[PDB]
Length: 188
Image (cartoon, helix red, strand yellow):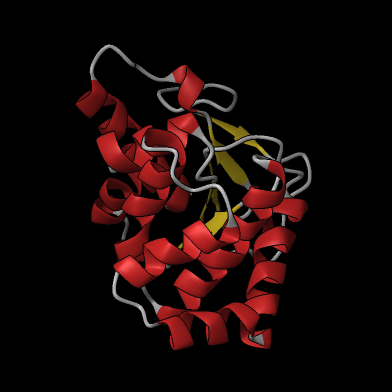
């Protein structure tokens, strides 16, 4: 065919019931994720081609960067709870991978303060039970698909994007191919 299992995507041996429609996993420690965010704007181009009435979900993962990786999953929970994903994503990526100025929970917090979230508001979120289960949700979704790698995208809890099987000579063509595959899978 044109789209083939094992080529632009793989199928889960054990599908996940009730999973979010488009589920993306990343780490601020993940080099391809940096690219996906900063250079390729993958999430955004997928969105642009998705049928509407479709929800997009993105979660952080623990298995990179040890202790700080976990801090980062909790901070992403804070970002989701406060609705400030779009203000912290770039400085978190660059603070971890570019300038390497994020070395502790306190430095992560600095990024939020500098993004304009108030200390009181961050620390209250950071410590809230609404942030605890949000962390729990992130871990559970990753657990459900036995996730050992990022970046990763899952469609309807059954299909997994396979970027290794797509053109990389041209970055724009890679993105469109990636986004069209998500759309195809979503209509499946």
